[PDB]
């Protein structure tokens, strides 16, 4: 779902950037490791939605931090 | 027993570095030995310090014949629910897991000057995961039978304030090590993917071992 | 600083093994620490000993504010004579060689309780070799300027007998290491053909002691 | 017979751990031996305990010369209908199967001090699969000829309460083992696909062996 | 503490085999347990014996609260000259070697009913390699400071004759094991080329381990 992979990619890169903005070193490969996905480009939609839940929660927590 | 270095230099007003420059003893070792935490001491060190401070070892070594030996349960009554609240994303012990309960028995064989030794049993249960900082937390335990061990408290408070603090340290350190050991065997590694402050990435293991659980009871107030 | 565990046990007749069993401490460590030989002591050890012996750490640790420091000349005045003959019969440094001269000054600071400290220079020259054993001979050095060290004797015997013996042991070791380092470099190894020892090893084992009115023991 | 450790330390008020710290005996072994269940004991153990408690073996060991030996039917009259109501999804013995009937004969060769031995026959029939917890159940049996074995009850109650409890334990344990053995041979493996509570996956076999069937009759009340 | 089986059946006049046939206990285990040497026993075994003999455990077990714990020197003062006079052709410990001297310290922490414990030091030296038979020898040791340990003897003789014999056995056995251990580490294997009597071939090691060194002193007469 190239539209989903762009949304997922934008959020995971946003999460990486926010971590770096927080001063916490962040790399895309690690945030992909959080999703434990082997290929972001090819994934089932439900997994993109499931991944979002992980990133959004994490993104919000650094906000509180 | 404990060296009174901290009390000695507080009374003198001198600093550890100043003493180290005077007695030619390594700053790190001397500052560690200044704290009662160090368990080993050198004869050269006691000679140099006693001479520098112009005092006999009497003032250097605070000794009380009442020996408090502590033993812990080989198997405790511990339940640790695992809550997967993004420990990796947030390095907080609460995010990694939570102690449902942690109760066990701490046997204290208090020994007077005479070989006569009195044993006190402590039903100690986990009470709360106190959050000292946003970064780390301290587990807090409580003695259910502390009222029974009122005589133990009488013996604890019968010692000097410095020796009382040394016991509290020893109890806290043993308890921390024990709790961290149990938890690290019960909880899988939860590595932190993103380092906080980019300084280092720490696995939950490093956090729980770093976590220092200090027992809280009227038996041990200070 | 003088552990009196040894003295205390002689007072109470308590065997070292008996104390080790009662205080749950290794016999080897307790016996090593008994004559204050080890330079490291565990807080647990002293705590257990004090509680067990019903003593304050005062009766365990005897300390005299006075401090003695010994500095040896970087370059000593030494001459060597190597016989190379008779070492083979049985370990004997004297047959293998001997030190014709080994005069050198040792700067000794006797520090008083007052920050001020007193510097005394003693010149010790090779006097003879002590035949303590046929296998081992200990070099003897005599103080030439004992006049400058008259106060040195007074400070030395001002300390307790145990402390005096401690000093004598330390100075003896230091002198032995000094002379062995100096000599082994100028001495070729001789194999003990008559379990296997090289004259170098002999030099290492051979010690030296300052025989003087200032240090009689 | 049984060591009176449980009764001894109840009277003393001491805890097993406290005794273990005193007599240098392993906590697990000592706590097991504290219960009358242990079938073996060490002279070292009896020496250390008798000395610690400052008591002769008389008090330490409670012995009644009346020996109750139990034998069970090689072949019982057992009918076990299989009703597989989702045992794999719900771990309840009821869901796995149900005992239509389980009657058999338990021969008890009660022996007095004298070699004179009296044998009592027990027509014991399954009565109900009592559900102790939502997780596990206890099979309940009943003696049809218990009124005939009224003399047996007279002999049972003629013993000490501790020894009576020890017999009840022995009878229950033998009966449980027997019943679980018969059922496990009669019922195929019904593995539990989903670990119970997710903590561990246990097969019906493990459940029935874990199941403890205690006989219920006026002969054995306590 | 020791089971008084030997004394019990001596008084009854019965034989171990006869008892074993009665209580269904293995002859070897029962005969070993009849001797005080056994360090382990079964509740089933005590139940059966107490019932068969119609006696309470009081008579069955003899316990004296005075506990004699023995400790030996980690390093002894031992000199063992090697004189190989054809040990392989003649299997005599004397032919294999000879003890020049074997002195060491045996610490006995005698404990009364109260935790108060008294320690007695035994300067024990090898005296003679007593030759019990032409085949084997017994090493004999002697306590130099036995006169100092006169109080120990007072405590030893204060016990029952059976318990005294049990101590003597324990002391002998520990001493034998210790001496054989030291010697076997100090003496190389001296295999016996010709089986002794042709029945079996035994190495010096087997001979010294078989060798049983019993201490001899007025402290321990019987």
Image (tube, coloured by chain):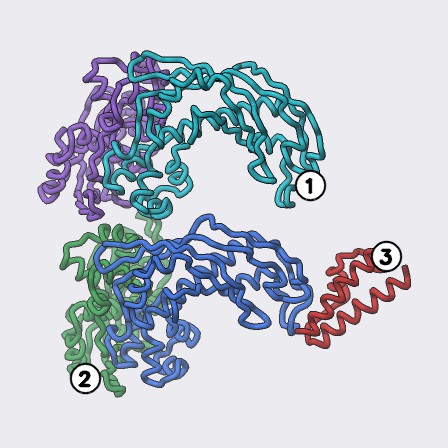
Chain colours: A red, B blue, C green, D cyan, E purple
Badge 3 is on which residue?
Answer: A45
Quarter of the image where the N terminus of chain B is located: bottom left
Mark 2–mark 3 distance (CA, rounded to whole Å): 97 Å
The quarter holding residue E198 reads top left
Name the one closer to the observer, B150 or C191.
Answer: B150
For label 2, the crowd category at 10 Å Cα-Cα, with few meaning under 14, some 14 to 19 and many 20 or more, is few
Q: Residue at x 62, y 42 (%)?
A: D200
The chain letter for the residue carrying disc 3 is A
| Residue E82, disc | none
* Location of mark 1 (residue): D194
User: Which mark is in front, 1 or 2?
Assistant: 1
How much space separates mark 3 and mark 1, taking CA atoms?
A: 28 Å
Tell me what residue is drawn at x 64 percent, y 42 percent.
D196
Q: In terms of depth relative to the viewer, which is nearer, C28 or D113?
A: D113
Labels 1 & 2 near each other (Cβ < 8 A): no
Residue B55 x, y percent position in the rendering: 25, 79
Disc assigned to residue C148: 2
The chain letter under disc 2 is C
State how many labels appear: 3
- Figure quadrant of residue C133: bottom left
Q: Position of residue A57 (x, y in %)?
A: 73, 66
């Amino acid at each position: 779902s190239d539209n989903d992979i762009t949304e997922l990619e934008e959020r995971i890169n946003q999460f990486v950037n926010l971590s770096q903005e927080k001063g916490r070193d962040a790399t895309i490969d690690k945030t992909m490791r959080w999703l434990k996905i082997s290929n972001i480009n090819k994934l089932s939609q439900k997994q993109i939605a499931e991944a979002h839940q992980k990133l959004d929660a994490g993104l919000k927590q650094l906000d509180s931090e | 027993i404990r060296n009174r270095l901290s009390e000695l230099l507080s009374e003198r007003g001198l600093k550890i570095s100043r003493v180290a420059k005077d007695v030619k003893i390594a700053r790190s070792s001397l500052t560690s030995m200044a704290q009662n935490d160090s368990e080993m001491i050198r004869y050269d060190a006691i000679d140099k310090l006693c001479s520098y401070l112009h005092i006999s070892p009497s003032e250097f070594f605070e000794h009380n014949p009442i020996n408090f030996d502590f033993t812990f349960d080989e198997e405790p009554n511990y339940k640790i629910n695992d809550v997967f609240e993004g420990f990796e994303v947030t390095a907080n012990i609460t995010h990694a897991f939570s102690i449902e309960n942690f109760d066990f028995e701490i046997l204290v064989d208090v020994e007077l000057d005479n070989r006569q030794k009195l044993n006190f049993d402590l039903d100690v249960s986990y009470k709360e995961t106190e959050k000292i900082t946003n970064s780390q937390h301290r587990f807090i335990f409580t003695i259910k039978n502390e009222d029974e061990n009122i005589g133990l408290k009488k013996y604890v408070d019968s010692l000097s304030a410095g020796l009382k603090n040394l016991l509290f340290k020893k109890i806290n350190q043993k308890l921390s090590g024990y709790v961290s050991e149990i938890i690290v065997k019960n909880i899988d590694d939860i590595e932190e993917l993103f380092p906080n402050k980019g300084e280092k990435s720490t696995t939950l293991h490093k956090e729980i071992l770093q976590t220092d659980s200090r027992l809280s009871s009227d038996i041990f107030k200070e």
